[PDB]
Image (cartoon, rainbow, N blue to C red; front, top):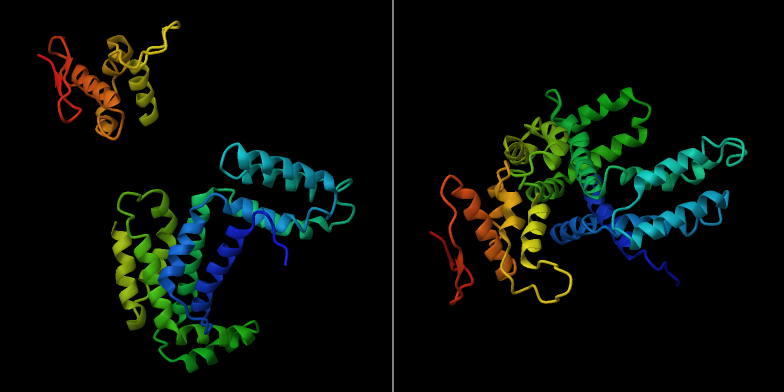
Amino acid sequence: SPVVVGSKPAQRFAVLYGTMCDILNGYDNQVVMQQKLKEFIEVLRDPKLPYSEFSAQFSALHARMPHKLDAQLTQVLERAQNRGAEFPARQLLKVFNKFLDDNVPNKTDQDLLKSTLEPLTSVLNLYLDGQKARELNLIADLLSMYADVECQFSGRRLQDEEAILKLRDQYKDNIQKVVNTVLSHKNVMSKNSLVLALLDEYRPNKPNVGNVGKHLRPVLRRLTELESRQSAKVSLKAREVLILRTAQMEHILRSSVVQSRYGETGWSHRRPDREVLKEVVDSKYTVFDVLTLFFAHEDPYVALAALEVYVRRAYRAYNLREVRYHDEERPYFIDWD
């Protein structure tokens, strides 16, 4: 059977969410939850996925309604794929609205186009905030899926499912909803372990209390409410979480290394010029915040340059004197007085 040129990451993303969701819903499809979750995080972290999702759906939607829109979308995708890495989700959202519901006369003869381009509109809205934002949105949905079902069981002294079923009688929609929620609660043991694994993966929230922290804050606070014996351990673990220039200087270091001076090719050997690195030593910023990793993991000359920058900025009130770099075993030996 034939396949799309770029649809392999899209085909593996869709199944991994489905496999985890089945455990949350209460479906019999059991699997090695650890391996699939690792695979799920890996696919959400690759930037090919937004393009892969678009390419899989758009291939069948090429010869759909007015091609004028279909062709302009393709040009933006192809340019952004090779040139750059981030998906043009924000640009693609703008062009869909401008043609579908907006261009009522030419583009949409009758109000039909909104339904046709709906999967595309769902894709550029999911990535509108960004790639890692998509990674955080889905994690939140899994946590929320767990809480939505479990909250009623942790509800106002109702420990009985049959009493809860007779309580569910209030809603007409509950006709099919009743059995679904009960099915999910029966397989809570597997559900708890999935959430625990999801919480363990996002446990290094200690440094990133901002971006991933605030994003997980609402779903986490609802989980802490689940005092019930079954969810008691997960509530404790959840609570643990709630309790919880670089480039600019690199260029200056490298510009002192090799001074262009048109006419000669080999300026690599030439020592770093004082005036070149004078800009940094006379600055006001806490230069020393980043510097600590530049005498590190760089060219032994760039490591030398970083050492010099440090001396001329750390002992400023002191007088300027001769600098000597020696090479023995370890490329480090600097000398000043």
